[PDB]
Protein backbone atom coordinates (compact mmCIF):
# COMPACT_ATOMS: atom_id res chain seq x y z
CA UNK A 1 0.00 0.00 0.00
CA UNK A 2 2.83 2.38 0.88
CA UNK A 3 4.75 0.47 -1.84
CA UNK A 4 2.25 1.55 -4.49
CA UNK A 5 1.53 5.03 -3.08
CA UNK A 6 5.21 5.96 -3.17
CA UNK A 7 5.45 4.78 -6.77
CA UNK A 8 2.36 6.80 -7.69
CA UNK A 9 3.88 9.98 -6.29
CA UNK A 10 6.97 9.06 -8.31
CA UNK A 11 4.87 8.80 -11.48
CA UNK A 12 3.39 12.26 -10.91
CA UNK A 13 6.93 13.55 -10.34
CA UNK A 14 8.65 12.11 -13.37
CA UNK A 15 6.82 9.38 -15.21
CA UNK A 16 8.20 5.90 -15.81
CA UNK A 17 11.80 7.03 -15.23
CA UNK A 18 11.08 8.25 -11.70
CA UNK A 19 9.45 4.90 -11.02
CA UNK A 20 12.56 3.11 -12.30
CA UNK A 21 14.76 5.32 -10.11
CA UNK A 22 12.72 4.78 -6.95
CA UNK A 23 12.59 1.03 -7.56
CA UNK A 24 16.35 0.76 -8.06
CA UNK A 25 17.00 3.00 -5.05
CA UNK A 26 14.81 0.86 -2.73
CA UNK A 27 16.38 -2.34 -4.08
CA UNK A 28 19.86 -0.97 -3.37
CA UNK A 29 19.19 0.81 -0.04
CA UNK A 30 21.51 3.72 -0.81
CA UNK A 31 22.91 4.77 -4.16
CA UNK A 32 24.65 7.63 -5.91
CA UNK A 33 23.25 9.49 -8.92
CA UNK A 34 25.81 7.73 -11.07
CA UNK A 35 25.02 4.28 -9.67
CA UNK A 36 21.34 4.91 -10.32
CA UNK A 37 21.92 6.13 -13.89
CA UNK A 38 23.77 2.86 -14.54
CA UNK A 39 21.28 0.63 -12.77
CA UNK A 40 18.37 2.21 -14.62
CA UNK A 41 19.62 3.53 -18.00
CA UNK A 42 18.15 6.95 -17.20
CA UNK A 43 20.48 9.88 -17.73
CA UNK A 44 22.30 11.22 -14.71
CA UNK A 45 20.93 14.75 -15.14
CA UNK A 46 17.46 13.21 -15.00
CA UNK A 47 18.23 10.82 -12.14
CA UNK A 48 19.47 13.87 -10.29
CA UNK A 49 16.45 16.05 -11.11
CA UNK A 50 14.15 13.22 -9.96
CA UNK A 51 16.07 12.81 -6.72
CA UNK A 52 15.98 16.50 -5.82
CA UNK A 53 12.23 16.39 -6.48
CA UNK A 54 11.83 13.47 -4.08
CA UNK A 55 13.97 15.41 -1.61
CA UNK A 56 11.77 18.54 -1.87
CA UNK A 57 8.67 16.29 -1.46
CA UNK A 58 10.49 15.07 1.69
CA UNK A 59 10.30 11.52 0.33
CA UNK A 60 14.08 11.11 0.01
CA UNK A 61 17.10 12.01 2.03
CA UNK A 62 20.79 11.82 1.32
CA UNK A 63 24.15 11.68 2.95
CA UNK A 64 27.25 13.33 1.51
CA UNK A 65 30.81 12.05 1.01
CA UNK A 66 33.83 14.19 0.14
CA UNK A 67 35.68 12.71 -2.83
CA UNK A 68 39.24 13.35 -1.91
CA UNK A 69 40.83 13.26 -5.37
CA UNK A 70 38.70 16.28 -6.42
CA UNK A 71 37.40 17.81 -3.18
CA UNK A 72 33.80 17.76 -4.45
CA UNK A 73 30.93 16.01 -2.70
CA UNK A 74 28.82 13.22 -4.06
CA UNK A 75 25.52 12.17 -2.45
CA UNK A 76 24.27 8.75 -1.30
CA UNK A 77 20.50 8.90 -1.64
CA UNK A 78 17.89 6.80 0.07
CA UNK A 79 14.11 6.71 0.15
CA UNK A 80 12.59 8.12 3.36
CA UNK A 81 9.05 6.86 3.99
CA UNK A 82 9.05 8.18 7.58
CA UNK A 83 6.78 11.10 6.71
CA UNK A 84 5.17 9.49 3.66
CA UNK A 85 1.74 9.22 5.42
CA UNK A 86 1.62 12.95 6.13
CA UNK A 87 2.84 13.55 2.56
CA UNK A 88 0.10 11.37 0.99
CA UNK A 89 -2.49 13.27 3.03
CA UNK A 90 -1.15 16.76 2.33
CA UNK A 91 -1.21 15.96 -1.39
CA UNK A 92 -4.85 14.83 -1.19
CA UNK A 93 -5.98 17.88 0.81
CA UNK A 94 -4.15 20.15 -1.61
CA UNK A 95 -5.66 18.46 -4.64
CA UNK A 96 -9.07 18.67 -2.98
CA UNK A 97 -8.98 22.38 -2.30
CA UNK A 98 -7.58 23.01 -5.73
CA UNK A 99 -10.98 21.59 -6.67
CA UNK A 100 -12.69 23.69 -3.97
CA UNK A 101 -11.63 26.95 -5.59
CA UNK A 102 -12.85 25.90 -9.03
CA UNK A 103 -16.22 25.35 -7.36
CA UNK A 104 -16.03 28.84 -5.81
CA UNK A 105 -15.30 30.27 -9.33
Image (cartoon, rainbow, N blue to C red):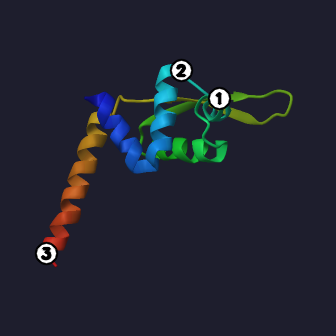
Residue located 51% across and 28% down the image: 25
Q: Which residue is mark 2?
A: 28
Mark 1 Cα shell of 10 Å, populated few (<14), some (14-19), many (≥20): some
Quadrant of the frame with the C terminus: bottom left
Relative image position of residue 23 (x, y in whole percent): 46, 29
Depth check, mark 3 against mark 1: the one in front is 1
Residue occupying image coordinates x 25% and y 56%: 94
Mark 2 and mark 3 in contact? Answer it, CB < 8 Å: no
Ranked by sequence position, the earlier of labels 3 and 1 is 1
Q: Earlier in the sequence, mark 2 or mark 3?
A: 2
> Where residue 20 appears, x then y in whole percent?
49, 35
The reply, left or right, for residue 87 in relation to residue 71 is left
Measured in 3D between alpha carbons, the distance from the residue under mark 2 to the one under mark 3, in whole angstroms, is 47 Å
Q: Nearer the viewer, residue 53 or 37?
A: 37
Q: Residue furthest left?
A: 103
Work out whether residue 76 or residue 44 is closer to the camera in this orientation and state it.
44
Q: Earlier in the sequence, mark 2 or mark 1?
A: 2
Q: Which residue is mark 1?
A: 35
User: Which residue position is annotated with label 3?
Assistant: 104
Mark 3 → mark 1, Cα distance in angstroms = 48 Å
> Going 59% across and 47% down the picture, which residue do you hit?
46
- Residue 56: x and y in percent read 46, 46
**Contact between labelled residues 1 and 2, with CB atoms less than 8 Å apart:** yes
Query: What residue appears at the point 46 percent right and 49 percent down from the top-left corner?
Result: 14
Q: Nearer the viewer, residue 92 or 25?
A: 25
**Quarter of the image that includes the N terminus:** top left
- Place residue 42 in its image quadrant: top right
Residue 72 picture location, percent across and down: 77, 36
| Crowding at mark 2 (Cα within 10 Å: few <14, some 14-19, many 20+) | few
Amino acid sequence: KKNTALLDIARDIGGDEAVEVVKALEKKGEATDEELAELTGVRVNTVRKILYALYDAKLATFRRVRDDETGWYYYYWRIDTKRLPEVIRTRKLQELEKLKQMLQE
